[PDB]
Image: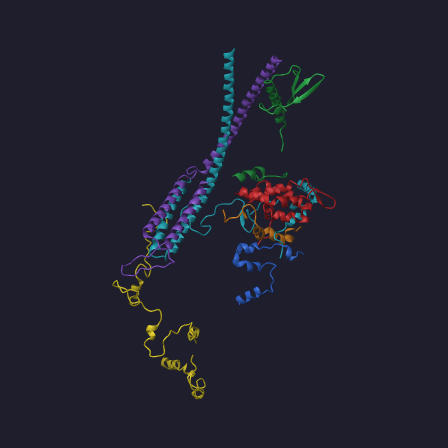
């Protein structure tokens, strides 16, 4: 098993489709394994989607 | 020459290898290997 | 002659409807507004400079008015949204219950005048003024 | 949706050798350069050198990298344990000269 | 959460020393695979002559597609006809720009068809250039051969002028030897 | 055309190579040794010679200045204008 | 390279259309339909003198015409307009045959050069050993 503190992560499908700028670093980071699904950012994203 | 990169001109880029079909050959490695 | 591509003599273009080359004020007859609030009269002389506040339209009342009721004096309130809220029988019949659909807030139990008299009878003398 | 073909899979893999971050990823895994299977596969992939196979090569620096990697394969020796000796310094070479090689081929691009 | 890069093809597992040593005796005797040594033979070229790679379609002998085949309008189609058509297309583009400026100067609400005409005139210009591109490529190959011939003949000239300088300098030493004799 | 010629000629595009993937011609070695004999012989003609050093053997890329039963010293020059080594 | 310059010129000349539209949309002013109507402007609009405005319009149009001139001349000087691919191949084979022929011409030229090389070799070696025996 590879621990989370020791890997570099990127989603070049996401880079080709959306492209990364300053305005989408947080939901780019939301696809990373670093992101916690139980976070306030994701739950308020669901609130604003609702 | 400041907005174009060497990513898919000299070599296949990472996204090229992902959306490419060697990547799904890895998933379907069992069907490609079959011997009668 | 030599034909050139997509240069078609039978294809014709018209002006915009309305045409912004003309004075659309004069086209739709907004001349009365334009000459009623024009900064200068249309003979070369300067017109009277209208005042920033509504003193001219509140000067025709006999009252205690010496200042301007604004947002910042603390005497007014923001009634814009409450101001903006919204809700056989012939046409005539339908229209008197349209006129009578709001009168229900005028009588008791909404506006009991006996209770109004009882609360207004508790008023004592004088008002504390700074 | 057809299944992959051997020609297309081998074409994509041989062309991925131009991506020398990818061969760095391949040759930083201990089970790949030690295995003689990869040696024999890279010797087998020399059919992309010759036409009509070479016509379909879109990124010919992959062919360059293939010949460069097969330069070590005749100096490779496989033992009874399966360790392909002489291959311990190849990852050293790849990680040392990767940025230099891709810089040179970018200069050839320009 | 997987690896960044795809692994090598599973075909790698077939390339062992035993398989390589049984390969030449097999050679003495989209495929129909009959044994494990069929993967040690290079695969044939595609029968359809189209192959898929990196999420795209490729052809073994590619050809320039047409405007009708790609869903656009080709106005008009030994290249002098194409060169005069290119001149006509340039003049039509300039006239279409002038007409676009006129339409914008009187009513900018029918600009859509004029922008569409400039769009199709430009793709026709670019497609005519792409049709002329193999001819210019073959001219470039001819230029490569001619420049190689020029370098070859320059080497001929410099070698022969060195040789003739040797001949006339030997004639000079012969003449001064006759003078000093 | 450049990349097409490289790939269809060598099977590879022409990139700098630092590892194995030169060779000095022996006929060129023989020719250079003959013209090096010619170079030492074209050099010694312009120089005066000592009387006991008149025995010189002219072969093998160099000159053998010998004094019999005493010594034999062998020297080479690189060109016309450089002194002997 | 010539078709490359042609494609560059077309892209730049369409960009000249775009830039001309940009300037004429952003840097215009206000004019009188009649003299009676008031004239005014703001700080958010680039007010320019009309005479140099017309001068810049004229020089933009001259740039468009001049770019059209370079494109037309470049089309006229495109490499190869009357020969077809059959004449191209009939040039290709004679060019390779002349390349082989001039390489053979180089072979005999170098043969003559090596003849001169060993001739002057024999001359200078005879000269040096003769004068060395004379000086000895």
Which chain is rendered red in the image?
D
The image position of residue D3, as x and y in percent, is 60, 52
Quadrant that contains the N terminus of chain D: bottom right
The residue located at (54%, 42%) in the rendering is D107
Q: Position of residue C82 (x, y in %)?
A: 44, 75
- In the figure, what tint was chain G given? purple
Instruction: Report the number of numbered marks.
Output: 0
Identify the chain drawn in green.
F
Residue C37 vs residue F9: left or right?
left
Q: Outermost residue, left direction?
A: C43
Res C30 → quadrant: bottom left
> Taking C62 as reference, is E156 above or below it?
above
When the figure is inspected, residue D73 is found, relative to residue G19, above or below; the finding is above
Give left or right: position of C9 versus B28. Answer: left
Q: Whole-percent x and y of residue E37?
A: 67, 45
Q: Is residue F4 above or below residue A7?
A: above
Which percent across, then down, holds residue E122?
A: 42, 48
Looking at the image, residue A28 lies above or below residue E27: below
Chain A pictured colour: blue
User: Visible in this render: residue C4?
Assistant: no
Q: Colour of chain C?
A: yellow
Residue A37 visible from this viewpoint: yes
Q: E36 or G45: nearer the eye? A: G45
Which colour is chain B painted? orange
């Amino acid at each position: 098993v590879t621990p989370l503190d020791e890997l570099q992560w990127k989603s070049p499908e996401w880079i080709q489709v959306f492209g990364l700028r300053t305005e989408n670093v947080l939901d780019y980071f939301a696809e990373s394994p670093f992101f916690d699904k139980t976070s306030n950012n994701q739950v308020i994203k669901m609130q604003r989607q609702f | 020459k400041g907005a174009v990169g060497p990513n898919n001109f000299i070599w296949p880029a990472e996204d090229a290898l992902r959306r490419g079909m060697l990547a799904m050959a890895s998933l379907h490695s069992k069907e490609l290997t079959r011997i009668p | 002659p030599s034909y050139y591509y997509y240069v078609d003599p039978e294809t014709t273009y018209t002006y915009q409807q309305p045409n912004p080359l003309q004075d659309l004020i004069s086209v739709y007859g907004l001349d009365d507004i334009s000459r009623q609030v024009a900064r200068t009269n249309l003979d070369g002389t300067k017109a009277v400079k209208l005042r920033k506040s509504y003193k001219n339209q509140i000067a025709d009342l006999s009252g205690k008015f010496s200042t301007i009721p604004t947002r910042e004096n603390g005497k007014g309130g923001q009634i814009a949204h409450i101001l903006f809220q919204n809700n056989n029988m012939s046409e005539q019949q339908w229209r008197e219950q349209l006129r009578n659909r709001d009168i229900a807030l005028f009588q008791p139990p909404n506006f009991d005048w006996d209770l109004c008299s009882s609360v207004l009878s508790q008023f004592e003398r004088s008002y504390p003024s700074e | 949706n057809p299944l992959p073909t051997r020609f297309e899979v081998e074409l994509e893999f041989i062309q991925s050798l131009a991506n020398i971050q990818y061969v760095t990823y391949l040759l930083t895994q201990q089970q790949i350069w030690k295995s003689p299977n990869f040696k024999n596969y890279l010797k087998y992939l020399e059919y992309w050198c010759n036409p009509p196979y070479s016509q379909c090569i879109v990124y010919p620096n992959c062919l360059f990298i293939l010949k460069l990697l097969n330069g070590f394969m005749e100096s490779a020796i496989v033992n009874e344990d399966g360790l392909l000796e002489g291959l311990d310094e190849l990852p050293k070479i790849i990680q040392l000269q990767g940025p230099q090689w891709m810089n040179e081929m970018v200069e050839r691009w320009a | 959460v997987s690896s960044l890069y795809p692994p090598p093809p599973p075909y790698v597992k077939f390339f062992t020393q035993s398989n390589l040593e049984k390969l030449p005796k097999y050679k003495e005797k989209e495929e129909e695979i009959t044994c494990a040594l069929d993967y040690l033979i290079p695969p044939p070229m595609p029968k359809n002559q189209q192959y898929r790679a990196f999420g795209s379609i490729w052809q073994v002998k590619d050809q320039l597609p047409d405007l009708e085949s790609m869903g656009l309008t080709q106005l008009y189609k030994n290249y002098q006809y194409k060169i005069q058509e290119l001149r006509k297309l340039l003049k039509s583009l300039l006239l279409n720009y002038l007409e676009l400026i006129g339409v914008l100067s009187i009513n900018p609400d029918m600009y859509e068809r004029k922008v569409e005409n400039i769009r199709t005139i430009l793709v026709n210009i670019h497609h005519l250039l792409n049709e002329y591109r193999p001819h210019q490529s073959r001219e470039s190959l001819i230029m490569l051969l001619e420049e190689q011939l020029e370098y070859k003949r320059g080497e001929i000239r410099e070698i022969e002028q060195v040789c003739k300088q040797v001949h006339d300098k030997l004639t000079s030493i012969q003449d001064t030897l006759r003078t000093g004799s | 055309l450049v990349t097409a010629l490289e790939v269809l000629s060598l099977g590879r595009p022409n990139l700098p190579t630092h590892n194995f993937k030169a060779k000095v011609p022996i006929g060129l070695i023989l020719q250079r040794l003959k013209d090096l004999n010619l170079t030492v012989s074209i050099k010694i003609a312009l120089m005066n010679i000592p009387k006991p050093l008149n025995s010189y053997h002219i072969k093998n890329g160099r000159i053998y200045f010998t004094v019999p039963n005493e010594f034999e010293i062998q020297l080479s020059t690189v060109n016309r204008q450089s002194p002997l080594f | 390279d010539r078709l490359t310059q042609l494609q560059i010129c077309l892209d730049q000349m369409t960009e000249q259309f775009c830039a001309t539209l940009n300037y004429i949309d952003k840097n215009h002013g206000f004019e009188r339909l009649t003299v009676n109507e008031p004239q005014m402007s703001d700080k958010h609009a680039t007010v320019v003198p009309p005479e140099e405005f017309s001068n810049t319009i004229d020089e933009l149009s001259t740039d468009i015409i001049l770019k059209t001139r370079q494109i037309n001349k470049l089309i006229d000087s495109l490499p190869g307009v009357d020969v077809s691919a059959e004449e191209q191949l009939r040039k290709i084979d004679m060019l390779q045959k002349k390349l082989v022929e001039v390489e053979d011409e180089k072979i005999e030229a170098i043969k003559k050069k090596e003849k001169l090389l060993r001739h002057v070799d024999s001359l200078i070696e005879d000269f040096v050993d003769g004068i060395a025996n004379s000086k000895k």
